[PDB]
Length: 10
Length: 212
Length: 220
Image 1 (spheres, rainbow over the protein chains, first blue to last red):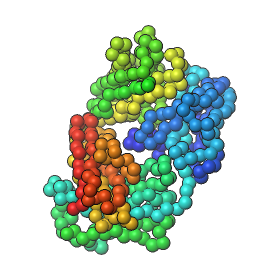
Image 2: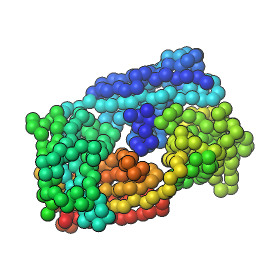
Image 3: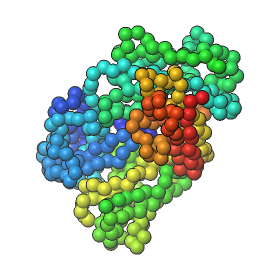
């Protein structure tokens, strides 16, 4: 799922 | 809309190894697919256009293949800087759609964390809150345990953790655990400690200070 | 060079409208179409719409009635506007340009605009030093940092010594506190023998609240 804080999938 | 399925969601490999990313389309799209790289806190970076056509400024280690419904993005010799998410995009059918993405993690040797502890500033104490920070720097793998103790009392529920994305230079992680107390509670106690557990340590590491 | 520069991050109330400006350079808007793409936790990357060289607009199906794209050719600006926002519209919004005037392979992206949809108020952060000492020192190397606490919404930018210090810097992802405010730390490792002659400053900038703070960190 995409994370807005790092712009990375978590 | 065309459904693009990327598989797997996560790839973990060692440097110098070859790696392949998959993108399967819900129906035939010919060779109308583009690939993207997204690094930490970055915008998408165009890598490959139309299945296999190369892009200016993109290293030669990046290549793509496939046609119809089955596509593959390849890296012949993966480097530390390749740590990123990879996305496919189709444009045979309007509207253009993207896949859910594949994450590229890198393996390396076990590295123990350097542990540092930071007491609250006097500045913060004036506002009535006390944050105590415990830093785990440059370690691998990602898994670690941080336990807080105030005057030998185990803390629970009053700390928060944050972990950096994988370092694109040395493949390590860093973690911060912050213990948050009220000023009153902080002042009523003396010994503050975070004990750290990790694979690279033969025994737990405890950094601690005394208030004052 | 070809560049796309978007307006700053900001908070948008539920049901209200979103507005973003994309200013371009290195090419003319009369020659290329500017696309709009967003990236949400829910749906990942998602093409929203485009405005072409002639001013024609195409909007993706779910956004045809609440999305409006305009531009000013002489000012090299593109204007993005979306109506009636809900919480799941919270995402990073990019503008982008394709390799050719008619195509859709995006080689040039704007830096992104992180839009937060919430009914809360904007709050600027307090900045506190993480002071170096004997308990942040290891083998001639000292750790120090800044605690950036109690702000809303995301994001904050942190640099050190106005960008002249990048080696050994880790700025941690923000975490959401129970108060509903974010909090974050940024650390850097330096030689302990430099603490006496070098000044270390974290440059904190929270654009949504127009809060700019330079915090010097020193041994206590």
